[PDB]
Amino acid sequence: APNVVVTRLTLVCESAPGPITMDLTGDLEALKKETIVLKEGSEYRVKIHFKVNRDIVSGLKYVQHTYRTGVKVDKATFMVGSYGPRPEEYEFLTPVEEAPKGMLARGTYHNKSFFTDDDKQDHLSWEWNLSIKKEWT
Ligand SMILES: O=C(N[C@H](c1ccc(-c2ccccc2)cc1)c1cccs1)[C@H]1CCCNC1
């Protein structure tokens, strides 16, 4: 096992009808197929579940790249910090954002996330898709 193990991504949205999450321990190619649904205008946060196993890690960063076909990447970096080893997993949450609204805002966005640190270590790099819809269905 590695020192840092990213286990789960969750979109914390209080107005959502059900859970919006994805297991990050399985196959990484199957993650692209899975599409995450977010109603337009919804307030949300990105939650990263991860474990520290042996030693204190420092300088953790969450890096998120959002792609729409034919558009320049929308980048965002979040400082995660230092964490010590323990059996229970940790939870890092981004600040609240508001998903865009309107027909021009609806559609599927292609995300590539990076859980890394100051040492540019690849704790986990994965792809996932987010669909902005007029309603939750
Ligand atoms: O719509 C915006 N950016 C969008 C976007 C859409 C969705 C996300 C996302 C990804 C992952 C999770 C949650 C949400 C991220 C960005 C675009 C990206 C690339 C080309 S446009 C502006 C307008 C108002 C809201 N703040 C930013």
Image: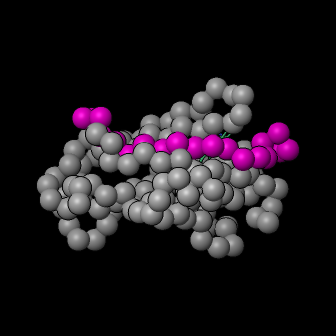
Magenta region, residue range: 101-120
Quarter of the image where the N terminus is located: bottom left
Q: Is residue 37 magenta?
A: no
Q: Is residue 107 magenta?
A: yes
Residue 69: give x, y in percent of width and height. Answer: 71, 34
Could you say which quadrant of the image residue 84 lies in?
bottom left
Which residue corresponds to the image point at 20% horizontal and 49% vertical from the top-left?
57
Residue 56: give x, y in percent of width and height. Answer: 16, 52
Compared to 27, does 80 lie above or below? above
Which colouring convention does the figure follow? Answer: one colour
Compared to 110, does 92 lie above or below? below
Which residue corresponds to the image point at 69% horizontal and 73% vertical from the top-left?
17
| Residue 96 seen by the camera | no
Residue at the extreme left: 55
For ligand 1, which image quadrant applies? top right
Residue 39: give x, y in percent of width and height. Answer: 74, 58
Which residue corresponds to the image point at 20% horizontal and 62% vertical from the top-left?
53
Compared to 55, does 118 lie above or below? above
Q: Is residue 52 left or right of residue 50?
A: left
